Amino acid sequence: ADRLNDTANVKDYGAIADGAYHPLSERFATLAEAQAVYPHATALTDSIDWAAYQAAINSGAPHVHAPGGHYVMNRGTLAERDIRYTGDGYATRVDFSLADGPGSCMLTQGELVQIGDLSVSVVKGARTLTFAAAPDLAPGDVVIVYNPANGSWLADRDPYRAGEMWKVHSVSGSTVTIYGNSSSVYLFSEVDVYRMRGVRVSVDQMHFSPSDTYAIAPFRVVFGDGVKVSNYYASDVTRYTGLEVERCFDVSINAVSSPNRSPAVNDEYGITISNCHNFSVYGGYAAATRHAVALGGMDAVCCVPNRNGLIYGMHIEGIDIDSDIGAGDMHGNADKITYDNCEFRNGVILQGRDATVRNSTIYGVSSVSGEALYGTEVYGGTYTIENNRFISYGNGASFGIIHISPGTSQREALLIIARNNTFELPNATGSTKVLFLRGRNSPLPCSVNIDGMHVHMAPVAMQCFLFADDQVAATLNSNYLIIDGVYGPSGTYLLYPTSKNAAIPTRQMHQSGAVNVTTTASATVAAPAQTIRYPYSKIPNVSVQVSSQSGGGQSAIGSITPVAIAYNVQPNSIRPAIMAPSGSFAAGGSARLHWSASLDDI
Amino acid sequence: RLNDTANVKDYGAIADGAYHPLSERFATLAEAQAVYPHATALTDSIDWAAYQAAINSGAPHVHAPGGHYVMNRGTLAERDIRYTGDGYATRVDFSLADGPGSCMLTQGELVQIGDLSVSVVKGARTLTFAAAPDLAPGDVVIVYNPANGSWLADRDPYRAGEMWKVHSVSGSTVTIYGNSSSVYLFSEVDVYRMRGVRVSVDQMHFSPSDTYAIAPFRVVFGDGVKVSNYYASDVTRYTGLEVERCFDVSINAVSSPNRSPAVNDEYGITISNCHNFSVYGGYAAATRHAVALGGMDAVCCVPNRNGLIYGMHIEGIDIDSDIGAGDMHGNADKITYDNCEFRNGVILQGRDATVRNSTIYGVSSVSGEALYGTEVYGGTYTIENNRFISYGNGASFGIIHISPGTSQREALLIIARNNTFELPNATGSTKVLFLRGRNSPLPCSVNIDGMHVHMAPVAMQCFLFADDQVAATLNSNYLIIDGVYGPSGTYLLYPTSKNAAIPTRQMHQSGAVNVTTTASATVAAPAQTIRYPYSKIPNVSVQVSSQSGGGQSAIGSITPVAIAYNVQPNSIRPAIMAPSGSFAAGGSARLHWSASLDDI
Amino acid sequence: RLNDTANVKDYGAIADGAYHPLSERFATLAEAQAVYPHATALTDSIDWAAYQAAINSGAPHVHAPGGHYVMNRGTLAERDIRYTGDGYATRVDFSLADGPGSCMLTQGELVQIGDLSVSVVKGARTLTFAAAPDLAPGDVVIVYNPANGSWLADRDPYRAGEMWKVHSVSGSTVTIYGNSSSVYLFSEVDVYRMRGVRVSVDQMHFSPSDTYAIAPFRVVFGDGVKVSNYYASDVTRYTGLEVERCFDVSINAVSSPNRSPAVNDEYGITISNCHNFSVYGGYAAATRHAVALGGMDAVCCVPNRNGLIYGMHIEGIDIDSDIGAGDMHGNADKITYDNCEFRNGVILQGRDATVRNSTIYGVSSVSGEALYGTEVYGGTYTIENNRFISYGNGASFGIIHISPGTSQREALLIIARNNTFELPNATGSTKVLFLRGRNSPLPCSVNIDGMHVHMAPVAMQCFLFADDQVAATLNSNYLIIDGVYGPSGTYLLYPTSKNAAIPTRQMHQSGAVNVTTTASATVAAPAQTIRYPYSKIPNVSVQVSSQSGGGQSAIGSITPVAIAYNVQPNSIRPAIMAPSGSFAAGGSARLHWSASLDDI
Ligand SMILES: [Ca+2]
Ligand SMILES: [Ca+2]
Ligand SMILES: [Ca+2]
Ligand SMILES: [Ca+2]
Ligand SMILES: [Ca+2]
Ligand SMILES: [Ca+2]
Ligand code: NA
Ligand code: NA
Ligand code: NA
Ligand code: NA
Ligand code: NA
Ligand code: NA
Ligand code: NA
Ligand code: NA
Ligand code: NA
Ligand code: NA
């Protein structure tokens, strides 16, 4: 920068910003005259507000301030360097309604360039990269490995491609020390390697409205490193999205208010994070037709998964539509994304690998089923669902309240961890399934650990706490199904048994009871069948014992030493009994028959 | 205006910490008014006159450079506005102001619209009006029940109602973002449109009126309100900050202490009748409530709802009528504290109240209640992953004490999972979780799973105490008490006539004891203590092995038949019997036992 | 002051990334000093001279517009101050500065006051002085024990003490916000008053001295410190940011990487002897500790206390002496990490240390320890709702490894509830949680509940290993191991002579096996494997049913009597006996069993 100023105020550069379109023709008779002031002008139709804005950026000033006003922009702006954008709050409205075509937005874009190849394959947990020749990298650069094969992350969509970003600590010869560690295997002959020298971009106290005609965010950062978004507003988001960051590293978004209100067609996102690493979204209010927070991807080099994302302390709202979908998104190109301490009105999506939601209030979508947590684009790894309060008005019948359904694209074993959750299901029926695991010709094991599943307001026996099958295959491939720490209506199966899950090892909650009996003149005195509140999927492991009715001292019953046995054991009932060693009891004696049950295959 | 930023000093402020009346500068009121037309009296301060002049320019951004502004009148803005200062050095001091509006007030728009024609059900995602409504996308629509106590009877201004942002309107049908928490009968509610103001404050320090109880910075009918890097001092009467009847409010990095006498309020920051609010990343301190969640008495004084308070350091002081530093008045629905520190105490009231992930101290009362609530609507009270520390005895009030009354409107469920309790002064009267209905009209049920008591020096009364203070019995669907640890002799549930009929699930326990046979038909082991006694006779098992665990069948010539010879809530005698005849004296065995309750 | 915003370029800075000595502008030192009285030599840089001149103006707000400021001296401010820049483009570079104070320093006031007359107890909420104290509301009062190692003996500067904000003073009694974590004997402590500076920094980039180990931006004796949108680069020696002996510190959206050789420290950001601090919303990276929680050696170098680190991405690198990226030195009390990513490793040390809701990787050592601590005071170490991933073997050091020594001051309780452990390189020597006292003087007790091991390829050594490396026995009140899942053959607790006497509670297990009778008095099933072996003989039940579950009583002419024929820690033989005589061969039954331990 041989720049003349450090802060550029857009109005000093000629902006009118009175909410009307003012072409350069209002001020200049010819294009040549206009270009003598604004060399970047291409036509006299170009708006004065745009010409001024781009002039301010072209000054080189690190800080570009747009004072209060309604800037009517019929072209996008471009910055390719570190920049801090500010306004006066909601009063600074930057409106791209009239802009059309690629780049119809406030775009800031860093540098991405392909570098030399690796000579050593990256393993999971690796903390160095080794190159065939000394790499063109310096401390602080971001290095990206990228697998250009379609679907190399997940086959569900071609742009779901594998790869990863790391910040560079140091370089020694041909070995690069990276911060963090590798989530995945990257074979050296399969991946291309890039260097990202990202731009540091900040936005604060500004309000944007997007193009009416072209689906693009009104403020967009590409190849950012150290991106800061605060106190950011959108309005008239009538097509696509209010904000997007793409192929960025180290992104912090807080106190945003960026609602989408577009027709439900293909996207409809409040804010959009695309192919980013080390991002945080907190302290704000997100709203949309479909996804208030959208975690997606685009189709370009280094379109690697969203990874290492923390979305927390957010109010996340959507609306009822025909094809109901959760307001908190996660597209399948996701790894190590965690929602924590959020409200979802309504619904959350867990997809990709290593997906987590904790400490949240989560509503079922307004479908017949009322699924509150849904995912199909499932890579595998661990899906963690902990300390949430779920509320649904649906029936959980065709799709579960939690519904996780991997398909042929699954790449690793899946483990679903669901611990200490509450489920408020006032419209539950005998078909309701609280957690529904449904493989769709899944190729690898899918296993479940439920521990702490408290169902509130259910008016009748439900189908089950857990439903587990494969819709296509003859059996579900799984290592275990654990169902523990449940509460709900009597008659609700722990696991609904089918031929598809009968072979899978299972652990099912311990249950117990006792019943008073009066003896008959019989060798065996069996209680009537005692109901098991939450039926097992198969005959449980049981105990039975005898005491007095009161718990006072008692040994013999009449002249008989009573021998406790399990006379009948069903998945849903038990008949404890006592037998005489020889002969028969006398009629009229008294006892209490105790029983317990569990399954513990793992 | 020429400038979209108005700097208060550029409008004449002195801001040197002294009172400068306009009479210092102008000989007559007319002369003053020729410069400041808003001036009313020559006593009005120059700092105030400048500040209102700045706002009156219409500038979206009003900046008060460093200085001590001595304001003896309040300021008013009724539009979107961004306020800034230079940090703690920008001190806007309303000490000398008295009367209504003795503050920096920013206020939006609220107007009544037409009535609904369809009752709103729980979970509803549209509203239907009798005629096409005067709403546009982005407006906030508020339903309001003007009947006193229509949320909770405890206080007349605890009225029912709800705010939603408008997505779209088709005919008479409005599509709302989010969903309805409640039933709203169309003949019982009024409907309002709120077109709120976007208000920001950053890098400013306020001091309130000395005489009139009003926050020094107040936003009413805000939408998209942003507060950061905000300080208060000399908060000697009421509060340091208030937002009222706002939607979408974000408060971070605040340092707004209260230090007023304990009388009627004493709030660090105050959130009154707001929806979709967040408070994080800050330090809150007060005499009573460092963070206060309250309400006022005006139209659309609906419950605080959908609130997230997280990552906060929340401090109070010891007072005579001890009360938690983290407040929740009864006009609260779906308020969640997460990852906070409370030195000392939190309150859970209203409906669907939550605290998770927090370090929570007992107040400095005899009882040392750490979590308390009485103005209880119902729904689910969730208490998870906390570490509680109390120096009290938990006797009259529990360490967790939840006590709904006649005002309860829905069944209550208390969920207390994976909590730790550090109770170095526990006694034989200590109750860890005390559910006490006060003539409650509806069921109150409990699920405790994971309750680890540390440092208790003696047997406590119980992990759970559950009763109704007035009624003959407690109305409840279940009491579950599982995953506990504490001193031996502590009841899982303390049994009384008031709770005897309630279905209960109680932690599995077990043991074993070696015995030597006597020349008897029955050989009963000594009484084995049940560490955490049950509320009634448990469901039991008994078995027999060798003492070593090596192979053993017959004992002498006798096939031993395991039985439960006696069972108490606090002990058991497992035994073995001979099928006929007697054992010989001197045989050896080990008798095993287990116990649980599982009514639900 | 003539100025409220001072712009450093208006005060003369060039800031073009080159060193410009004052000699470029002034022929003589007399002329330089006439403009810049603070100039000491003509070699002093123009950028530095301008920056110090801007601070010396008294302006509350000092703005450094975009530029690369080449500072060959440090700056000093001793008052409330707001620093701003234009973002990453404002680069304040102290590379060329050397010696003490080679940084942007802002420092408040600390003075010794009068002594206490009453010892402070745990939970105390007032302080009583021998004479009326020199304190006012809002001040911070600090008690300090100057004896070396008075917090932990491990290091001399780990001294006891505490900070509180003053609410009010009545005679000689001070009312404090919050409460006392500790006992402070009045004869052992000195008392100080801290009148801290309110300091803010936003939108700035720093680089440190090349030669002297000091943060480039440093606050000492701050109160209400605010850091946001802060960057560092070329952190080649020590750290990018440090706050020291501050109260109420909020740090968000920082990007401050360290990249120094692994020698003695290597910290991204550093918090030293602070209270009521929060770090959130950012990205921290370093050679050793991305977030460093340490201390210095000076008066009032009290423990870090009441700290919340949340929603952070925390990264380190592989080094020879692997160490966790999320630090906690032993001088820590009530520090909580929540909802963070650790690539790789976290440390829990001091007292009352917590990590929840986090994704935690094992460091790149042979053992792959993910959570480590040895400078252990005691209290409660809470580990909840985490997902651990390690590529190590957990053999010499556990995945979680907590190892108090002789310096331990209070009983230790480790609470590990609902964690998941991904251990693809686990072996028969792997220990998930390893408690290892090193001649510990006080009890160390464990509650594991919910420990789910994923990807382990073989039986591990144990879920819990607990011993003392030095003493003949481990001093402990209890070891609870519940809610586990992992490979078959993995011990719940690995038994040794050192832990054999400790009360234990171990997960309930069960099974069943079909048998066909022989012509025998006793029909025993073969040994049934217990998936997770107990540390000693479990408490068992056994029963008999039909194989189908259909009705069955007698087996031929025999009433079957269930017994525990053999019980080992790792297997069981349920059996049935005839009361007299023998079964006939060829009858059918199903023998059920269960097991648990519940000493506590
Ligand atoms: Ca669209
Ligand atoms: Ca629908
Ligand atoms: Ca008051
Ligand atoms: Ca008190
Ligand atoms: Ca160093
Ligand atoms: Ca290493
Ligand atoms: Na022309
Ligand atoms: Na119910
Ligand atoms: Na008004
Ligand atoms: Na209108
Ligand atoms: Na309208
Ligand atoms: Na009232
Ligand atoms: Na009405
Ligand atoms: Na034998
Ligand atoms: Na040092
Ligand atoms: Na028996």
Image (spheres, coloured by chain):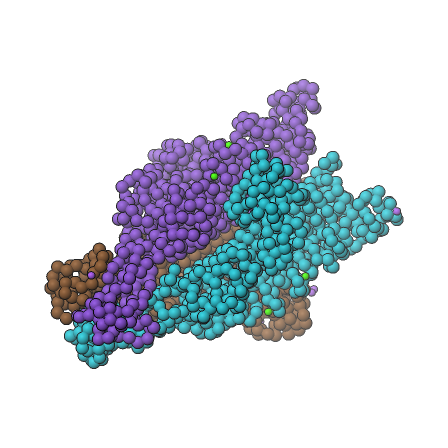
Chain colours: A cyan, B brown, C purple
- Viewer-closest of A28 and A352: A352
Q: Residue C284: x, y in percent?
A: 54, 42
**Quadrant location of the N terminus of chain A in the rendered image:** top right
Q: Nearer the viewer, residue A69 or C175?
A: A69
Q: Residue at x 67, y 26 (%)?
A: C20
Image height check: is B412 above or below A258?
below
Going 46% across and 39% down the picture, which residue do you hit? Answer: C322
- Point out the image quarter for the C terminus of chain A: bottom left
Question: Where, by quadrant of the figure, is residue B546 drawn?
Answer: bottom left
Name the one closer to the observer, C485 or C257: C485
Residue B582 visible in the displayed image: yes
* Displayed quadrant of residue A559: bottom left
Tell me how many marks there are.
Answer: 0
Q: Position of residue C233 (x, y in %)?
A: 59, 36
Could you tell me if residue A293 is visible in this image? no
- Identify whether C246 is placed above or below B425: above
Residue in the foreground of this view, choosing between A54 and A508: A508
Residue B147's place in the image compared with C241, above or below, is: below
Q: Residue at x 58, y 54 (%)?
A: A153
In percent of width and height, residue C424 lies at 45, 50
- Position in image of residue B172 (x %, y %): 66, 72
Q: Is residue C377 left or right of residue A370?
A: left
The residue that appears at 14% across and 60% down in the rendered structure is: B587
Residue C40 in the image: above or below residue B4: above
